[PDB]
Image (cartoon, rainbow, N blue to C red; front, side, top):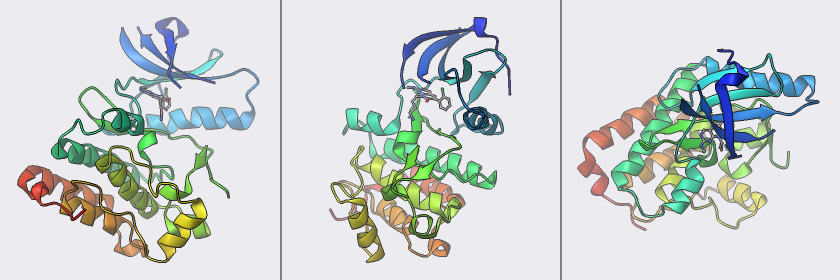
Amino acid sequence: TTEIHPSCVTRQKVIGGEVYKGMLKEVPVAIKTLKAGYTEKQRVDFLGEAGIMGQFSHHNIIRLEGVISKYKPMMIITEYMENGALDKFLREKDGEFSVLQLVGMLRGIAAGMKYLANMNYVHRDLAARNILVNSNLVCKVSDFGLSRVLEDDGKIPIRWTAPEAISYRKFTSASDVWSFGIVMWEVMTYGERPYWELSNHEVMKAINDGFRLPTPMDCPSAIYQLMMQCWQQERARRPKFADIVSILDKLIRAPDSLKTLADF
Ligand SMILES: CNc1ncc2cc(-c3ccccc3Cl)c(=O)n(CCCCN)c2n1
């Protein structure tokens, strides 16, 4: 990773230690800090996130500019994503995009996830809140935090998580595909919360009994079919990210295919 001198960085506004929007000398950056008195585990986890991010070079994965590790407070410096987190963005822009735009967002996310999977990285916490959006509507996977625990067992939420990951702690790229299907539903609904007010136990019971999320309004049939396949109980029946990228690319290149809507 690039070691950046603190004099080349100015923090301007808190946007999330803390996360700041700032400038790198100028280019806008996001800046995550670690506070004094951090433990050995905290340090390994913090610098670990940067270490992971530094091993990746892909359009749909947040870019690391560098780290401040020689000086305190320590910092991770990334590209700045002008539209922020995808979940909040969708909810504040409800109805404002074309179906083609929404599908193109999903293709980007899927391409990033295919790259992570092929680089032997299991995300475990894929959700729209962990995707960032730039001023070209490019969606990039973020959140490579090392220390994550499943809710009731950062907390990884049950209702984005595959059955096998919940039931026996088996997290793989196939569990990330399940999560991706939930992200598909988040995007096509402009940030609706999956399963609404069902409790975690009600969601798990529903899933195990064969229920799945219903079609979004105005959702292309092909898109609903794809998210449904991501939620197969049997991992081997789920598409790989390779398959998802291939299918989304075909739909985008023949965009009339998206005019055929699933019954709402
Ligand atoms: C608002 N635009 C914006 N742009 C870029 C980033 C980058 C980071 C980040 C991520 C990992 C390591 C280090 C960093 Cl700095 C970050 O935490 N936020 C805050 C929101 C994240 C929500 N999920 C970002 N926000």
